[PDB]
Image (cartoon, rainbow, N blue to C red):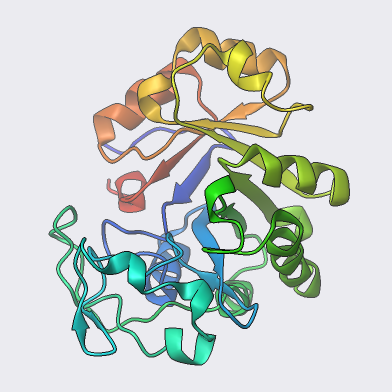
Length: 272
């Protein structure tokens, strides 16, 4: 029958619902909202003109993008189509929904573009006053000035949109980039942080990479252990792994004590 979840469990739609609909699109977010997810999960980058765009990558990815300025998007050229070198007026013209995704073959093919963060917010807020957000700052050290701004500007542009919409208390800012977490923690301490982890390491050695204890510890599912969950809980952290796409894996994790799930298939939770 249904997946049983504890009280206050956080069902997160990964990129809204990538398994079902083109990732990180208003269609995906609307579907996840209507399904009843707790949280819309999504990724943020910056255009040339300093608008916050919802996108997993700072470039148009070949898995999702049919063509840019007439060119077939492949592994060979995808990094040429750099969002940080493009004004949003140009970004918004490029379809990211009709191409078949080799890894999500049942995804619905519909016309879609990369939306502004502001549209995502204004869509979600119209539909729900209780929806939560988990937004990823897609920064890396090597990308500064090339793929996205410096840390302060990247974070400040995102935070400006959060404050404008008055969604601070329903917002978690997630990142792999410890620099973005440190900046957020010292400049905007009222916004909950999630620390994304994908490397080998003890929990202690991962946590020593930050100067503070974040709200959420968010590791690759393969890294999760009951011991680390219990340790994280004793520090007052919630544990929300990613990206978990089968019922049985979700059930195993729930039994170990996780506080939420990031999934491409949030419909798993509403299947009776």
